[PDB]
């Protein structure tokens, strides 16, 4: 059937879009391929933890996997599982593995909650056609408030065993002349204190994050999506994956949508149509839909920029071996609180999350997720044979990112007399993981594949809302930018188009 607006997906771009559409009085249907995560499983919790992964941990895989960095300690808990509609999808391309959330709330279900605005000067560099004053004056503040961003208590941080890991890297970094910053979060830090005090059920303090948090984390189901449903104008259908998009002869849109069960069995195909179509299927999902539509002839006027301009936000993971006298602790909160800010917009820029590790015993390891400035980009290319959009990114394209991360951490190692770990990312000596991505950006870049508000070139009433808009890099953790951009875009779209 027909509905005025359809939003594909339920991550950040989608959630913002649907809230504002509903507040404007536009009846809106959101289509989400994953689950609504609200049923207690066999342990009485909705989500599995990192020390007890089960089928809920994985989107249609036959074995659980350890968190990147943690294989040496967490492979012992891996198990064979039945392919299931779990929460975390490791999407494998030829030389890149991209990790994305699947469910109502998208990546907000599985992410570390870190809520960071980009440096304004870098924003202005990457998106020179966008008015940065309205972003910083209006839309970034609007996003932080509605996302429920909050700040850790510095005294508690300084005192608690749960953040020793962070203080160790802070102290090590300082010897190299490098500074740290507190990173705001959507995890309720007040709740986290009460966890540590034994007052409330633990989540961050019970090795949960990447397969969901049973408590504490204000994911989008709690914030934007709850509010959208509250408008009375928004509904969400789950286990509904959009496969194809076409325009109708009179200029609306028609979708083919597969409904599955949690075992992946096809229950129905349906046709859904609309006047307004908003893509919020993520960098991978939105881009795949549009590349497919262009190359199978259902949206024949899409431009050549659809599929282009993808990057992994410069993501590189690395680890240092601490001196024995600098243990990182057996008890590490699963929510990062500090970053190393070494980002000056030059090619040596690094913003590095000080990442906790879930092992639960002392390992002396400090883990980092570096965000770098690497101009290399990939392209999604439709494969008509398999009906998939393939990302053509090659491992060598991450060399600039590796080089920047290594220069930063080499400073820290020299100042402290420490060395890297070489064994965390497989048998082969490898200090820098260079073939994963938690922060996929691009594929439908703002102003390239779209106009400056995400209107898809070649089409009216067709919008892209999500990380596919971003030109490959933001220099920080991306969801605040995605949210704020979406606020800007949907507001304008509603005013001028709807
Ligand atoms: C392990 C991990 C840690 C991270 N930590 C942080 C952090 O601390 N801070 C930060 O800023 N960012 C972090 N991120 C990144 C952040 O989560 C993403 O940048 C953000 O979620 C992207 O939002 P989006 O709206 O583009 O898409 P997503 O949040 O990915 O949402 C897309 C949604 O669309 C659905 N979908 C896809 N295709 C279809 C289709 N065809 N039909 C129907 N539904 C579809 C998906 O299932 C999903 O629910 C992390 C991500 C991961 C995986």
Image (tube, rainbow, N blue to C red):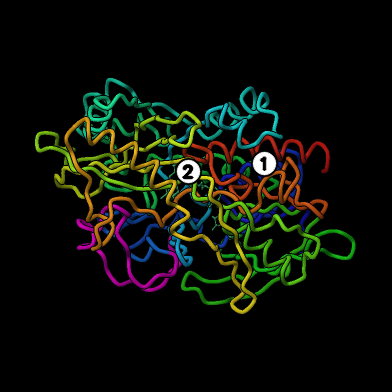
Assess whether residue 80 is covered by the magenta stretch: yes
Q: Residue at image x 83%, y 43%?
A: 497
- Sequence order check: which comes first, mark 2 or mark 1? 2
Q: Residue at image x 50%, y 31%?
A: 345
In this picture, is 347 found above or below 460? above
In the image, residue 410 lies at what x, y percent?
28, 38
Q: Is residue 286 visible?
A: yes
Residue count near mark 2 (Cα–Cα under 10 Å), binned few <14, some 14–19, many ≥20: many
In the image, residue 88 lies at what x, y percent?
43, 58
Assess whether residue 494 is covered by the magenta stretch: no
Mark number, residue 219: 2
Q: Main secondary structure of the magenta part?
A: loop
Q: Is residue 431 left or right of residue 104?
A: left
In the image, residue 338 lies at what x, y percent?
34, 31
The secondary element bearing badge 2 is classed as loop
Nearer to me, 125 or 110: 125
Circles 2, 1 touching at the beta carbon (< 8 Å): no
* Quarter placement of the C terminus: top right
The secondary element bearing badge 1 is classed as loop
In the rendered image, the residue lying farthest to the right is 250
| Image: magenta residue range | 59-86
The part of the image, by quadrant, that contains residue 190 is top left
In the rendered image, the residue lying farthest to the top is 155
Mark number, residue 231: 1
* Quarter placement of the N terminus: bottom right
3D distance between C-alphas at marks 2 and 1: 19 Å
In the image, residue 370 lies at what x, y percent?
39, 42
Ligand 1 lies under 8 Å from the Cβ of mark 1: no
Q: Is residue 89 visible?
A: no
The part of the image, by quadrant, that contains residue 80 is bottom left
Q: Is residue 323 left or right of residue 467?
A: left
Which mark's residue is nearer the viewer, 2 or 1?
2
């Amino acid at each position: 059937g027909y509905v005025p607006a359809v939003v594909i997906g339920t991550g950040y771009g989608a959630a913002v879009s649907a809230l504002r559409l509903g507040e404007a009085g536009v009846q809106t249907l959101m289509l989400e391929m994953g689950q609504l995560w609200n049923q207690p499983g066999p342990d009485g919790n909705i989500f599995c933890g990192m020390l007890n992964p089960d089928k809920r941990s994985s989107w249609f895989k036959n074995r659980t996997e350890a968190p990147l960095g943690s294989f040496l300690w967490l492979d012992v808990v891996n198990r064979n599982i039945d392919p299931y509609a779990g929460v975390l999808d490791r999407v494998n391309y030829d030389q890149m593995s991209v990790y994305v959330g699947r469910g109502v709330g998208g990546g907000s279900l599985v992410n570390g909650g870190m809520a960071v605005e980009p440096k304004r000067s870098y924003f202005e560099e990457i998106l020179p056609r966008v008015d940065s004053s309205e972003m910083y004056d209006r839309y970034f503040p609007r996003a932080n408030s509605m996302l429920r961003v909050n700040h850790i208590d510095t005294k508690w941080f300084e005192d608690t065993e749960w953040y020793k890991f962070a203080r160790v890297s802070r102290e090590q970094a300082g010897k190299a002349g490098l500074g740290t910053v507190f990173v705001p979060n959507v995890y309720d830090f007040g709740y986290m204190q009460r966890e540590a005090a034994g007052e409330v059920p633990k989540s961050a303090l019970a090795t949960e994050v990447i397969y969901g948090n049973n408590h504490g984390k204000q994911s989008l189901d709690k914030t934007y999506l709850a509010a959208a449903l509250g408008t009375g104008k928004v509904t969400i259908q789950t286990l509904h994956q959009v496969k194809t998009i076409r325009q109708t002869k009179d200029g609306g849109y028609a979708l083919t949508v597969e409904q599955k069960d949690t075992d992946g069995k096809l229950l129905a195909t349906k046709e859904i149509s609309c006047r307004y179509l908003f893509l919020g299927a993520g960098s991978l999902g939105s881009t795949e839909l549009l590349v497919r539509a262009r190359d199978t002839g259902t949206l024949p006027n899409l431009n050549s920029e659809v599929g282009a301009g993808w990057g992994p936000n410069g993501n590189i993971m690395t680890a240092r071996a601490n001196h024995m006298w600098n243990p990182t602790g057996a008890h590490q909160s699963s929510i990062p609180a500090l970053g190393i800010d070494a980002w000056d917009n030059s090619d040596s820029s690094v913003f590095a999350e000080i990442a906790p590790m879930p092992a639960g015993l002392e390992t002396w390891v400090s883990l980092y997720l570096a965000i770098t400035k690497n101009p290399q980009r990939g392209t999604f290319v439709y494969d008509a044979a398999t009906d998939r959009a393939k990302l053509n990114w090659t491992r060598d394209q991450n060399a600039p990112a590796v080089n920047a991360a290594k220069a930063l951490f080499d400073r820290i190692n020299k100042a402290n007399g420490t060395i890297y770990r070489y064994d965390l990312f497989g048998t082969q000596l490898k200090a820098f993981a260079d073939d994963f991505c938690y922060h996929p950006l691009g594929g439908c870049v703002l102003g390239k594949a779209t106009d400056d508000y995400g209107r898809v070139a070649g089409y009216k009433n067709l919008y892209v809302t999500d990380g596919s808009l971003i030109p490959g890099s933001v220099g920080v953790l991306p969801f605040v930018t995605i949210t704020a951009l979406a606020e800007r875009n949907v507001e304008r779209i509603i005013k001028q188009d709807v």
